[PDB]
Image (tube, rainbow over all chains, first blue to last red):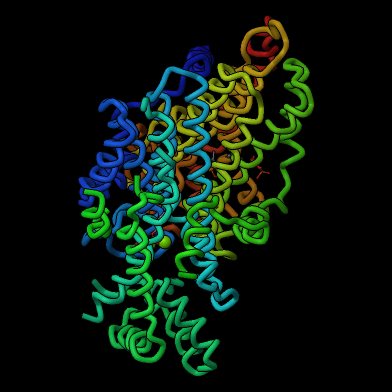
Length: 316
Length: 307
Ligand SMILES: C=C(C)CCOP(=O)(O)OP(=O)(O)O
Ligand SMILES: C=C(C)CCOP(=O)(O)OP(=O)(O)O
Ligand SMILES: C=C(C)CCOP(=O)(O)OP(=O)(O)O
Ligand SMILES: [Mg+2]
Ligand SMILES: [Mg+2]
Ligand SMILES: [Mg+2]
Ligand SMILES: [Mg+2]
């Protein structure tokens, strides 16, 4: 009966959770926190707020939600991408293991969700805040799904430029739109800045893909080891199909499929994209055109310190 | 000019997502759907609705939300537990890879969350369903994190029977309580009696202890993957704390060594089992523990837990 009394007191109570248990399972998350770039995701929110005007207490919460979602996404992305480093540091799953990292990352998504309720007391608004959160996280998982599928089942599907851009609108545009849509919904205060935040996500991503190869040609071109269907690689694959460069098209697939860390093999692929397909110049120029679409936006049809961010978008 | 036009169209529209795309991402999930148990998790929902009386359309969505969370939880748990099999079938991550499986599973978490807003249009009630959904998924992750922590840090921390039971209230109680708390908040029924959460908690507990018990018993009588996983099973927690108390130092260490082996070796697995069989009598202890738990419900004449 002391057993039953114990079982009885157990089931008539909320589940026990100590602050100690909380520390033990937050290890993978505390590790990625030791990484920079933070002050920048914070500079973008701060700038957009000059327009949205939410009180600083609400802006702090919007910011905590996004940081939890962002860092958790990277903890996961690194398992998904077999990444050994993130922001010059050893990846969490390599230290604590994939099991703990996945669980903790998923855990933080729900803490993030929890915080949405500290943004309002109003039910109509709260319901909309949750829908935005739910929607963009659904979008993030969709693009991430395609990026991962194209790569892992290559050459089953060779994405075209169009397909890549759609994948990026979901994948990368997910959190960008999330942050902005929350702010536009909490604003006490012109046209929606969503097309502009979308163009930013796109630029951010093609730039991430591009710089990952160009800095090795001049990091470690880890994208090649991953086998990622990046902007430069998507152009090269399609370009070779179109110009009938069979041998080169196949060599590109062969190298991607090696998941190689050999610097010379990676450098060969890059030099193929440089001189054979001209995928690097194409990408650098595609980036510039997108940036000009904003820099030449006088009539403010995209646009509402703003541009300073566009050139330091790599540090977010 | 034409490139700028295309980008303009793109950024002014919602992200494009086709049904073929939906089919691609769904592959790891669909693969697990070829699995039984469904006419039983759904059986419990049915039964309890006899007291809750939710209108079918609403009950089905609950059934849907529960199914997505459960199947998704299993996809991830198998990755976390390095499980090669689930219901006799090759686990999803061994077929589609860990990357796609993790992504798909999480996606389904959010799809499940989406179904929550289609349970009701009343803004007060909806908020409660979300808080419910949110709270239990958090407990689920807390328990899972602890079950994984003990295992992966062994032998840093060896839980006591009590710590184990608390871990289970979180991990396994989560989905059980989420299912019932939703149904109770939706119930059109005036006063369907005392809340059934205490009863669903005891159920969750019996369920997990029995799961750990059966993993070893169906191997002592004839794969015992919990040993290969190195899991702090209910019988294992009992054996470890039983040898520590009876000062049986060498048996205590032998148990730890085998769990730390992460072994698939039949002989060695048989060896750990014979220790629990003859040395600590942990399997008989577990069987009896389960029976006591059940008797709490069987001899519930004043219906304190039962409806
Ligand atoms: C969930 C998101 C948006 C992260 C995607 O990152 P990528 O795998 O595309 O590249 P890195 O962020 O690791 O540079
Ligand atoms: C959460 C635990 C311990 C078991 C999960 O699987 P079930 O016992 O519910 O069985 P199936 O859903 O896989 O049929
Ligand atoms: C997320 C939950 C609740 C499933 C936990 O199942 P276990 O980790 O106990 O392992 P299985 O025996 O169910 O495979
Ligand atoms: Mg990555
Ligand atoms: Mg990635
Ligand atoms: Mg398991
Ligand atoms: Mg498990």
